[PDB]
Length: 330
Ligand SMILES: C[C@H]1CC[C@H](NC(=O)Cn2ccnc2)CC1
Image (cartoon, rainbow, N blue to C red; front, side):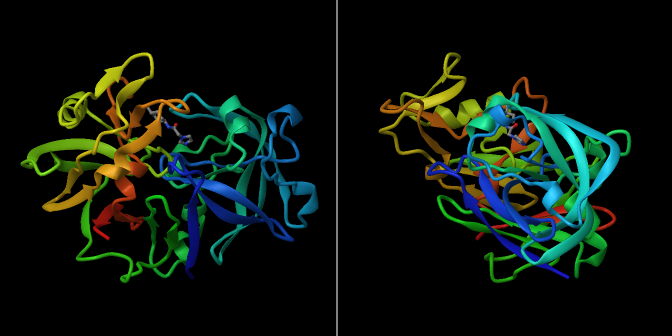
């Protein structure tokens, strides 16, 4: 089997991407944030504290003839941005782009933190990291991909995120029309539960490539590119007036700037992030200070190849017995 679904930016800055997902019978379609940095499929629901729902579409398990309470199971998750959610668990039929999994754990939120409430466009998350990170207790549950994998034509999914435009998540096949040149594959460590790999270095603009190992994660659920402070300083030093602002919470730059590109290495291959991809717009409405899309990972404890990086590539998440990652230009 295969599936193919369009993923759409939630706003004009590509702050996140949503993908429609069918849950239950009859189908309830929710727009979920596909997150290769986490491993829980959770949704706003009829069980979510009413004051914490503000415009989201909810899953109502009592209206699904295939929903079954997973008795005794609870979940609770916190993310790197400080947001969180928790609740109980159903199993139900879940389909993405024509690919159907029966008995998928659908984690129903009883509580969500303020940032989730405040974002009306995201109805939940669909985790695509390794199932070892799944938070369901006392019986850990599998991701949608983990459940689907054996049925797929090939045990892979691909992320093809757009810049200020829709893109595609495919399951079970590689669309050879969706990228240019060849896909370069690189080793993955699953030891921390992530799609963790080692970039071979970077360049800023038209500058020379610096060969250096940068261990990080391919994370569709993180908006920005988080790299070591040395690398980030080298980038922003090429933008007149750019500075790290403790009050804003990262590097900012004059909105009048033309940003240089940023290149990262995948083996001997190179992925070029155009400068425009690194502009996250005014820090507050009407400001001439703009927020940067490349930020320091110092104090995160891990480098994160988030959407800023991934949207410059066609990315293969290869879930074979020994997982790997593939990157192509597009
Ligand atoms: C320092 C960084 C700050 C931004 C963080 N972004 C997230 O946590 C986004 N997220 C929510 C759910 N899955 C992903 C990542 C760490």
